[PDB]
Length: 290
Length: 40
Length: 103
Length: 95
Image (cartoon, rainbow over all chains, first blue to last red; front, side, top):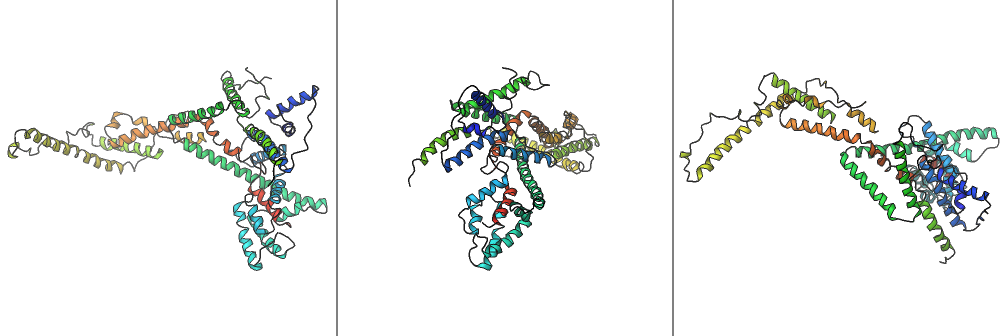
């Protein structure tokens, strides 16, 4: 059963084992059951923590239903893979990734008064060879000020930094003037769409190149895992993979009554159904009731 | 037995989702009572 | 590994072709009796000042040192046969059939 | 990937065409141990690349590290290039 905060996260979700939890709840409200009152409680810390642990119950089955585009040629299987993660994060309640990491910067550094503190409280979320490349620019601009640069914007010393911080961002490859003119808007919507269509060709070149960099790491992890495995004899592999299957059944068979472990062994029995159903008719595949 | 379904077969099997749920069922009631009993 | 296995068959074809060019017998050079010097001056046990039980120990070290010099003369043939084939397998073609695996 | 390595075990030279005793007795005895071990290495490599039932449990060593990267606190689809371009929107605006 659900606690109604799960079933509100599973309404716009699309995966299987959540939508059969929604369809079983939507059939119960139809049969004369009353809907629970949604609690207007658990102030800002518990409210943003339940969002962390309810969106991860939408992301986690959703990531497993997204086929990686490994060993593929072209940019369209990466634009498929990234768009499946865009539409997955939207079903889990996330916003656009540009909107969601810019929210992460202003959350970490609401009280950062110096530019060296905003470069060290948003350190985990910026590429480290870009964060370091903004420290040679911060140390160069610190020479002509000889005082700490403040996070003001109206300060002239911040404009001396942002004259050379923008100089890195174009050299990194990202058009900072098309980013900044997108999030500022424009007056007329005709020239607001000339910057919208140049932000979204950066952004589509942005979300692809790190969806592709996520694939090329899985391609290089699977090729180093396989080439470590092709060097073994076949008898070593058969007993190494039989102990790992035994110790991980045993970890789920010791934990009894837990929800995850009794759902784990229903997956082992459903894997064995797939092998048993293919073994009965292998030119057609598994048998679906249809 | 045989010939199960489609919506039973569409679920990804060994995803976590129930470790995340088991943590969220043991973290949230154990931290809802922490915020209502907190003085420095 | 594919090139080392292809270097070995180039060698085993070179060992065969420089053996068939001399038309020598097969088991001749693997038999250490053919490398044994039987015209050796064969030491007398009566000029060695041996005591009673010390003669069969004398006969064994003459038999050892003449068998161990016959094997060590066999190892010197194949150490010279190797370089005649290791320097003639390198000047070859290596047109070998490939292993029948399913396509 | 296991097909690309199978394809270079397909181009291996046939060593069983030299199993005759007229290749045995012509050859240096140490270069016949090396040849009979180079043939035993092919059967090691060929029987472990056709172990296709081992590839399902190999792909389960790639899944949990990948799925924990997608279980991010920011976004599933976030990466460095989006987060860099959203840093210049954050930095180069007035705080």
